[PDB]
Image (spheres, rainbow, N blue to C red):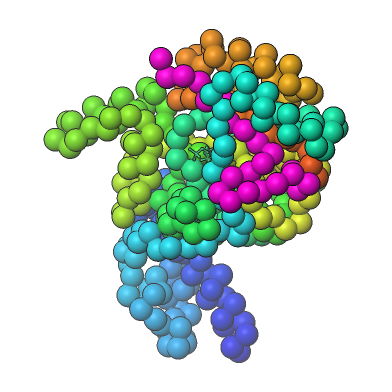
Amino acid sequence: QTAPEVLRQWQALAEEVREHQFRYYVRDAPIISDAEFDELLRRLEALEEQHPELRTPDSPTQLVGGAGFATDFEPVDHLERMLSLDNAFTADELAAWAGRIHAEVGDAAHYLCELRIDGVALSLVYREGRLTRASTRGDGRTGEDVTLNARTIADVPERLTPGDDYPVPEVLEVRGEVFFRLDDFQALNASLVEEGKAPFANPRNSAAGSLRQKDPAVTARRRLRMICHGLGHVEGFRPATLHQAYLALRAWGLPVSEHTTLATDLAGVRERIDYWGEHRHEVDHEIDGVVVKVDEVALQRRLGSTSRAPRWAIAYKYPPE
Ligand SMILES: Nc1ncnc2c1ncn2[C@@H]1O[C@H](COP(=O)(O)O)[C@@H](O)[C@H]1O
């Protein structure tokens, strides 16, 4: 019946209530019944009556009953630099990129291979198994805040899944690409034209437009998808290598692509690149390349991290036509 418990009760309740507000007005997918949700609000209202100090303009009860859900794209910092990637359009370049690697830091290096989904970058900051910030790439130190928009992608869990093999990290910042599916892209386009709205020229643009909405509910109606493909700052998770990292991601419920393979040498990499050149079309989303990452985390550190690029990864891009 004192300030310590009073503050605690309210904050816990506010967050619980605000989230149910957001899951009902935004999303159109509430996890609790309206019967229940109404009880929670009552409690918060009760405590608010008991203590008027808590009544504020930013409280769900005092000034915002179903409002206060907008995205202003406020600049926000990235915990770790989110760099872009060097590209390779010819085999010589790939070989050349992979000369430095095994000119220096020799052999222990395995090369993880992944598909290159040409979508929109997204950086999610997970704090204590909770999603607190979602941001765009921007310049690679600072991005735009799309917390609310990003909270609606079906593929992004709001909370990490606790697991024994992989304990939930304290601060997990994971990068990814938000994209459509080809079929869904067309459907959305036809929806827009029914509304007398201009359709999008390609899925990336659609990807992007759908994500950057001032009103997050708009973003909820559209079937945006997300893969996780990298990690930034992390506390309480020192994954030995990047392939093992994906194991943890899956354990926590984060989306991971199933076309990633591990290649011991350049020959294995080459095989994948030749393979994906002929089977790129078969995938449900746009794939314009193959990203080859020197996988061992330790080796990544030993290798450079140049201005606006990493030295331990090369993106082989296929010719458009
Ligand atoms: N393994 C990956 N698969 C698909 N896309 C990736 C992967 N890694 C990085 N990306 C994205 O590709 C971009 C690098 O190409 P770019 O931004 O054009 O310089 C990154 O900034 C990410 O948005």
In the displayed structure, does residue 15 sit left or right of residue 4? left
66 over 118 or under it: above or below: below
Span shown in magenta: 300-321
- Where residue 23 appears, as percent x and y from the top left, is 43, 52
In the rendered image, the residue lying farthest to the left is 196
Is 238 or 316 nearer to us in this picture? Answer: 316
317 over 40 or under it: above or below: above
For residue 270, say whether it is visible.
yes
Residue 223 colored in magenta in the image? no
Is 226 or 89 nearer to us in this picture? Answer: 89
- Where residue 277 appears, as percent x and y from the top left, is 54, 14
In the displayed structure, does residue 104 sit left or right of residue 177? right
Is 320 or 58 nearer to us in this picture? Answer: 320
Identified at 14% across, 35% down, the residue is 196
Identified at 61% across, 12% down, the residue is 275
Q: Main secondary structure of the magenta part?
A: loop
For residue 257, say whether it is visible.
no
Total numbered labels placed on residues in the image: 0
> Quarter-wise, where is residue 199 in the image?
top left
- Where residue 106 appears, as percent x and y from the top left, is 84, 33
100 over 50 or under it: above or below: above
Quadrant of image for the C terminus? top left
- Where residue 219 appears, as percent x and y from the top left, is 35, 45
Identified at 48% across, 25% down, the residue is 288
148 over 291 or under it: above or below: below
